[PDB]
Length: 89
Length: 89
Image 1 (cartoon, rainbow over the protein chains, first blue to last red):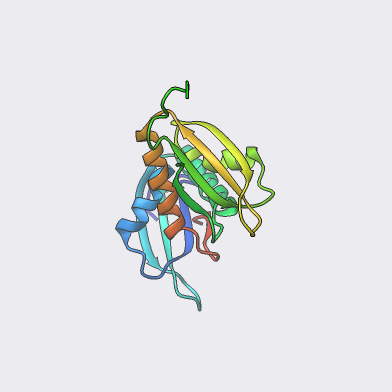
Image 2 (image 1 turned 90 degrees about the vertical axis):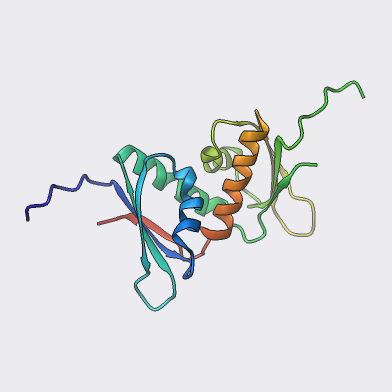
């Protein structure tokens, strides 16, 4: 209704982030999603469980789809609770 | 003993990765650690619990330290078990 049409698949929804995660801590963690990330909105997550949802708007569909893949791959393989990162002595 | 001195802090240890995670699945998930990543070795993790350790060798200390920060920030904030990523409708 008057608004420019939104480009399709340029914005990700990331739901169930930590309840007290700060905007600056989120943007530090999202840095590797690359220079395509334009804006971030952080709200309380809908539903019974505490959390936040982040709305991540990219400058292209290509930047957004790269970011979506990256997040999903990290989530499905690097999120082990006993994963430990250190300098190799 | 004959070997060129290793550069200091150019190699990360990532311990406690999933036991059956493949080399190709690890390298797909590590893609955002950026073009500094040169070589990856994947072994069984030492100790009582199942896992793998990945030895990640970077072309500079700058590439390695960026990669270490990125992994640690992702781990401490994006690893929630109910984190859900979708296209914003």
